[PDB]
Length: 99
Length: 99
Ligand SMILES: [K+]
Ligand SMILES: [K+]
Ligand code: NA
Image 1 (cartoon, helix red, strand yellow):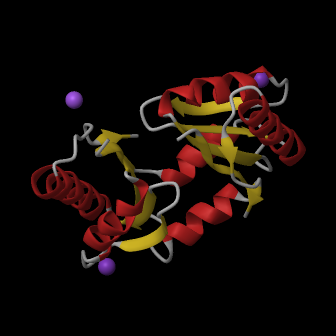
Image 2 (cartoon, chains in turn yellow, blue):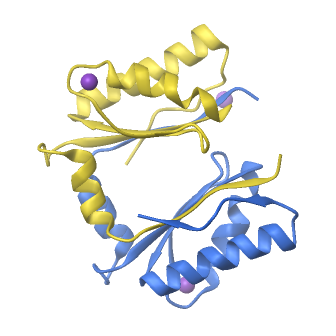
């Protein structure tokens, strides 16, 4: 399985960030990547179910999801994803990384 | 191969995007994702060696790279990565995409 799954130009990345943030320009962005890639939708379901979280995109081909909301909501969603995948699906996990 | 390879919160994504663009706020961002993930460093080498391209990050564990520069330099670097992985390493490749 040797594949480039994404080779993409974001032509207007500032516009793209405001589009993901929506009305709350004080928001944070959460990003998850995982394998097998098709399980991205389960991360998107967990994040998208939180009251102040919006999904920006889900990509089952690259295995990625991006979402936004207030920082506490985004951190809690990421923790919920790590916990579900580890405890319910036997996935190995990384630390919750912050920038 | 069941792994969460990235679970990341960006607290200030507008500032994050301007730091990645650097001096040229009218710049584009290129993003590559691939498998096996460890080869992401070769994509970052190819992009990074181009005179008008700055690497924003490379993550060998997730298989992703992000880099910035003028739109034509970013597109040329993506084409170069796609040609190298296909022709030198035998990788399957997605089309070069843009949003
Ligand atoms: K929601
Ligand atoms: K360079
Ligand atoms: Na570990």
